[PDB]
Image (tube, coloured by chain):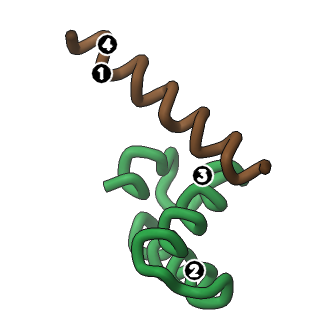
Chain colours: A green, B brown
């Protein structure tokens, strides 16, 4: 949901919402910084 | 109340940002 509203032109996600998505992934799923990063890459391709 | 919910979304986003920066 948060990836879809804060998306602009699909895969073009800027710098503030990428680390907002990373910290919400690392907080909600209790993952490391690597896990957050991989998940955010996948989610950005999906928003594309 | 709708305006309130949205401005509050703004506020909680801001608080989350400040918490990260600390």
Q: Which of the two marks, 1 or 3, is nearer to us in this view? A: 1
Q: Where is residue A22 in the image (x, y as percent from the top left)?
A: 59, 68
Q: Position of residue A7 (x, y in %)?
A: 48, 50
Local packing at callout 4 (Cα closer than 10 Å; few below 14, some 14-19, many 20+) is: few
Name the residue beneath numbered marker 3. Answer: A17
Chain letter, disc 4 residue: B
Q: Which of A24 and A39 is in front in this view?
A: A24
Chain letter, disc 1 residue: B
Q: How far apart are marks 3 and 2 (CA)?
A: 13 Å
In what element is the residue under mark 1? helix
Give the vertical position of A32 relative to A17 (above or below): below
Name the residue beneath numbered marker 2. Answer: A36
Name the residue beneath numbered marker 4. Answer: B4
Name the residue beneath numbered marker 1. Answer: B5
Name the quadrant containing residue A35.
bottom right
* Residue at mark 2 shares a chain with residue at mark 1: no
Q: Which of the two marks, 2 or 4, is nearer to us in this view? A: 4
Residue lying at 60% horizontally and 33% vertically, measured from the top left = B14
Residue lying at 61% horizontally and 87% vertically, measured from the top left = A32
């Amino acid at each position: 949901a948060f990836g879809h509203k804060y998306s602009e032109e699909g895969g073009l996600i800027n710098e503030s919402l990428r680390d907002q998505l990373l910290v919400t992934i690392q907080k909600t799923f209790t993952y490391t910084r690597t896990q957050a990063q991989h998940l955010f890459i996948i989610l950005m391709e999906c928003m594309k | 109340l709708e305006e309130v919910n949205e401005r509050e979304h703004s506020m909680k986003a801001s608080l989350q940002t400040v918490d990260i920066r600390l």
